[PDB]
Image (cartoon, rainbow, N blue to C red):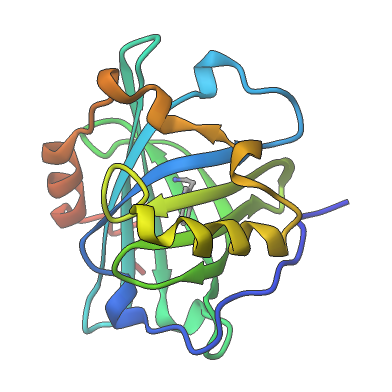
Length: 195
Ligand SMILES: NCCc1c[nH]c2ccccc12
């Protein structure tokens, strides 16, 4: 039952983490074998402002269907678990123009990160525990060769191996990212969630 609890990064430096963008390079979604509809290229853009708001905008592109989906996580600094890389966010699935399609609560747990290259995350919805995500994330489109070992270890903690995830860098050539929508939605106002 429920979302798994996983150990997370101690002394999480929010300032150094929530800036710039991330590419999702590898991931396991749920228990069943992955269908092509859930094989995507995801890039996200995020920020922490002085008011203490954290905002994270995702572009998810499915090469098989050649379609995009977008979602946004909203959180506040006081939603974090002390000094650890663990927090709850309201995540809103939205149209390109920001119109709300659906919303959910996501418990986020950062297993590890070096801030400037890679992070390893577990994301889960308490209302839909069957939807859980283990993700490898990079500051570049591919994982830097010199941190592969660090990523492998992090996945070790949670009973996983890289070759055990879907490698999104296999989509590779067909991958694309809606950078302009990312930038636009990040700056756009959402008074219903930014409160
Ligand atoms: N965009 C919804 C799932 C997701 C992927 N990576 C994340 C990092 C933090 C929060 C959610 C996520």
